[PDB]
Length: 221
Length: 222
Ligand code: NA
Image (cartoon, rainbow over all chains, first blue to last red; front, side, top):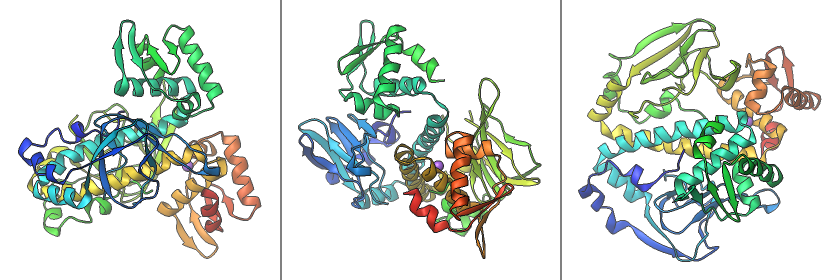
């Protein structure tokens, strides 16, 4: 499904208890290409993306950059603090603004309102089961199902309703979109060609219009 | 990298609040092949595998078994209960498999009585989702021998028994089943396994595997 957001994580937090964190929320602004955190850091902070776009990347073999995710407003960047950083977070847009707080403040705050952790537990529960079926999926899903799943994921988080459906301004490179799908840009470009000639989508340079999201859902399984 | 266990979720529970739940823990025993729960069922229970081994499978639309994971003693079977059906079926691998389970109502009233435990059950779920993100990161960078090494290491770390020659892993899986956990063809996985045996890293004993040199699998899994 959809990654962690502040709204989903803080939906059951009463307003007065959420107020207490605002003094401890730091605000940072990043320029294009600037790293918000790096792979393997040990700061143990919780970052909230407020404005802009961020990509979780992964420099590994031969120092080849590997796109893992792109994120938008309201989403938690990376993992919840408790374990070094599994990935690097790079600001896509200039004046990318993130709010963050140290883990000590969060755990003290959760200690003050332990009923909040009960409802956040249902969020990590619902997200870990969704994360598990994503792991089984990449074993048993062909590339059109994986393409349909990425386009649906991007549409639900970046989608703009247009006349013929939902436009998806992903603004990735053809290699990048293929990295999210999980195969070569050759295989993915052909799968996009099939989706287009079936009438399901249209390729708008670095945007994609989804004419028939209901068909992509069925193709996902 | 380890799936959820009772001890990991309940390490921070004071002894008093763990005793209050024993009134509501039901005990069921299953023989080999029996389903503990089925895919698409809507029970809101938390299952704890106490003794035996269990596999999580999902049946596709042409009724072919898809092996997702296998579990051993101490682990939570399937998902943790939540107020929104089960995404998989749990099948007993061993005879007289014993599971303990409690209804979500009992769990949530108990979390309500002791909300402080959910704070630290939150941090294990957080560190556990971090583990899966590391796992998804591997499958794009790992070739077939790396995933085979990691799969055999994962099985060895949970149901492995140290012997003088190394670690005996009585996995009891078919070549098709093991290849589904590795994530590629039965032929491709069998040949990678053969390379491991030819190199002296493992030996294939029926459906048990001795890992002569587990440290070699560690290096290869990177
Ligand atoms: Na693996």
